Length: 188
Image 1 (cartoon, rainbow, N blue to C red):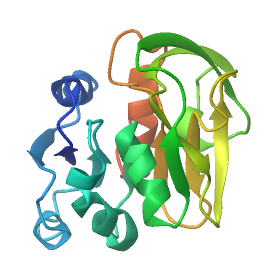
Image 2 (cartoon, rainbow, N blue to C red):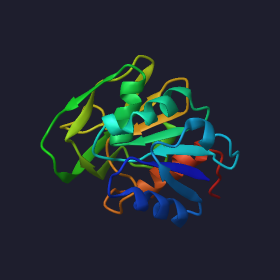
Image 3 (cartoon, helix red, strand yellow):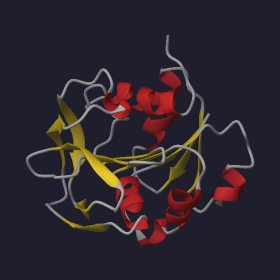
Image 4 (cartoon, rainbow, N blue to C red):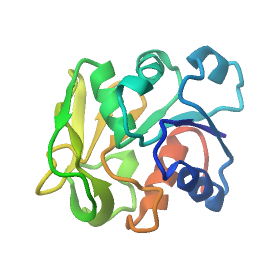
């Protein structure tokens, strides 16, 4: 199963339901849950750091991003938290508003397998990754966001600025499916 850290955003339940829909179990836990309690249960195959409003009140995600021995997906705030954790930079970009963003996939990566190189994703751009951490690379961009997605070149850590877990993201479930594949699931 996948543990979802609830960073307080309103789509946390859409993560659980989207995963269940492709036949993966998941559990929403408070974002203050210690990494050591998550990793005590060998049933936990991966961690998703959800979207939420305040990075200061998701400080515990920094420890999980740095020190977890399981695959991680950061969604919006989770993406930004991964960035900060590894000494990248994060800041205000555009106005607050959810919009369909045309996203370009810039390289061949496991996270976007069976996703067209061009797809519409549901995203806010209140905040964005400004400098990608050392030893990470950009997987995707839009006209307004240089870092729509990134991965750790040597750990199984993935960041998306957008929300794959809402139906408004084309191939959103596919992107979740792909992360689950890194976490040991097969979808034959």
